[PDB]
Length: 224
Length: 225
Ligand SMILES: [Pr+3]
Ligand SMILES: [Pr+3]
Ligand SMILES: [Pr+3]
Figure 1 (tube, protein in one colour):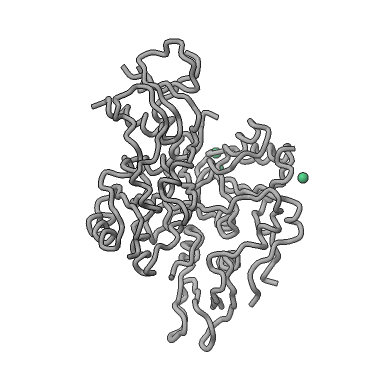
Figure 2 (figure 1 turned 135 degrees about the vertical axis):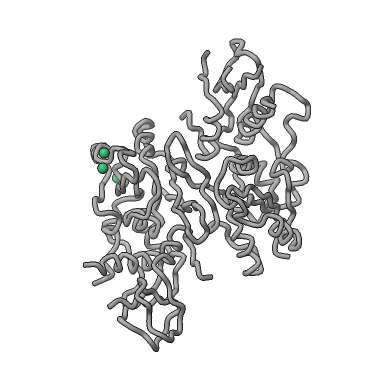
């Protein structure tokens, strides 16, 4: 079975019917690949399980020891949920043509020729490339994700939060996935800080969620 | 000098005034960098002297990093060249960041998309072999085997054929072994290139558009496989 130990999530399509999701999901399943309908989040522990307000960066979930390859499929680059998560996790976003090429070769070929742009940077006004650590035939996804420290690793972020609340949680989730620790508060309260995030309600300094996306698209700490 | 061991080519801007090229060219020179006005070709021999793939010139032993700078991806000849050689095409901000840090930083956060695939109908990523600080550009370029390494390609091509030569060059940079004859039809081969002439009737290998070369450049792969 070609897709043995591979996890797939499917994003978009961005443009109507640029690819047949259901057909491809079926082909993947029929070949030993697991399909995650909601996306890559099940690879990690739910940070919001405790409904806590001071959060540590994400840790790989037990179940991800069971796989060694992951991919998000997309007709082109986007800012949809599954896409950003993948960017956050350093999991390759690839063109559907990858799956078809795997079938054609009766194996899992190198995904690079099908590796989409990471996204469009408004700050830089260009499309950037994804930068993917190669899959090691030695590690499970659990090893890979455990050993990964994202571009925001170490950084301590204060997210100030007095429908819209879920939007905030998503930004927090991305910051955690990039390796930052995040404390959710209503005020700075004179707290020590590396960086402060608001949806836009005094010594860090401050920045909005677009900053997070730039970090996601560029896989860097752009405040640098 | 920060850029003492870096070679830079500059392309575009692609969009009017996206960046101040002359200002950037000046600052790189002021900071020790070599600027190649015509692009990256001077780093290799002149193959058009049925020659085999490109070899780096001894000159390139004197530098260990190279970049093509551009506001965004394009199909300009300098860009296409960088793609063929696996030299990073980066955003101008890269230079400003180096100045800011007083060192040559990781170019990675400034790594532009490789290009738009009309075949896949999407924008793809560049994939660059990391610069090993112990290796010169010569070592780097000598060790490289493009995605077209091995492929025998026939360029039937009987001022304007300069645009043609550009394609020939990219195939070689991609590591192909190329022979150029006005027409076939014996002959060897595993691929045939014609710039929309038509190509003779019967043939032993599929006919290909230059776009096929561009697709190989943008995806860094052998596409007909
Ligand atoms: Pr030196
Ligand atoms: Pr102009
Ligand atoms: Pr102008």
